[PDB]
Amino acid sequence: RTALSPGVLSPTRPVPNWIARPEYVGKPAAQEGSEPWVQTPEVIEKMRVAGRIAAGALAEAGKAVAPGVTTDELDRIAHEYLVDNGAYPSTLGYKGFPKSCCTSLNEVICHGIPDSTVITDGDIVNIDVTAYIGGVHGDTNATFPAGDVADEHRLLVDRTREATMRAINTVKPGRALSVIGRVIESYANRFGYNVVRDFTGHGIGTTFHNGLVVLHYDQPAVETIMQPGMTFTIEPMINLGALDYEIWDDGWTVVTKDRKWTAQFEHTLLVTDTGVEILTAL
Ligand SMILES: [Co+2]
Ligand SMILES: [Co+2]
Ligand SMILES: [Co+2]
Ligand code: NA
Ligand code: NA
């Protein structure tokens, strides 16, 4: 299997006029980064809806993962599920991003742009979808196998899912936020994998990335304590190879320097009064 290069992007996909755009659409930056980390009851309920819809679109696009399919095609299916359910694709026009989801094959760490790239037998494909509806965002991603994937790669994917679910299960009020990354990195290290550091989870609510940062590696200097009503993502990227990376000229696509493959899963989580709720549960 060759190292990837860019395909050709289809033209901007339309979303009907009636679907409210986030404020940042058609602007070079977003107005985000200083929003309250604890959401209102109202926002939380809205986030369950956005979460559910983001989960639906992910599951639909992942069902189309198969050798022969293009990445562009995955984006088409996600885009259509979001639009049919009344949601704007949060990534579309977010800091100039040109598509409705991120499609990250093989050695693409994250931020892959759906294009003419055709998926081949044995590939792994992460699809990261976000839904904006009722003034709020819901954010989820998963890596999907295409055809006969090598054992090495199935285990990576399975272990990355497990790391994510284990991190989720430690979410509870009064526990330090740093616990998440300690659990993730312990689990990756157990199988000789390396956890990506420069890319993180994030707080999410009425904004996409609200200023809260969730690290996926062990960093006990973070003193943040989880509180009921806080909403954030856990989205670890886990590398078979070294951490070093490059960004394509498209300004988005992050690829491992050594071209070894990498995997990721993501959910949007709520800290409840006693534990956690997965808002992007299928
Ligand atoms: Co990202
Ligand atoms: Co995401
Ligand atoms: Co996210
Ligand atoms: Na949500
Ligand atoms: Na990854």
Image (cartoon, rainbow, N blue to C red):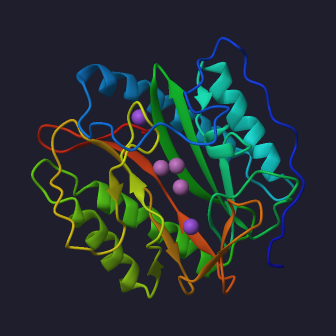
Q: Between residues 194 and 63, which one lies in front from this camera angle?
A: 194
Relative placement, left or right, of 45 versus 79 is left
Ligand 5: image quarter:
bottom right
Relative placement, left or right, of 237 versus 210 is right
Q: Position of residue 149 (x, y in %)?
A: 69, 72
* Count of numbered circles on the image: 0
- What residue is at 87 percent from the left and 38 percent from the top? 11
- What residue is at 38 percent from the left and 28 percent from the top? 48
Occupied quadrant, residue 94: top right
Q: Between residues 206 and 234, which one lies in front from this camera angle?
A: 206
Most extreme residue toward the front is 28
Relative placement, left or right, of 153 versus 75 is left
Q: Position of residue 143 (x, y in %)?
A: 59, 59
Most extreme residue toward the top is 18
Occupied quadrant, residue 146: bottom right
Q: Between residues 15 and 282, which one lies in front from this camera angle?
A: 15
- What residue is at 47 percent from the left and 83 percent from the top? 193
Q: Position of residue 178 (x, y in %)?
A: 23, 65
In the picture, which quadrant includes the N terminus? bottom right
Q: Position of residue 242 (x, y in %)?
A: 55, 87
- What residue is at 39 percent from the left and 51 percent from the top? 202
Above or below, comparing residue 94 to residue 197 in the picture:
above
Above or below, comparing residue 5 to residue 270 in the picture:
below
Above or below, comparing residue 206 to residue 119 in the picture:
above
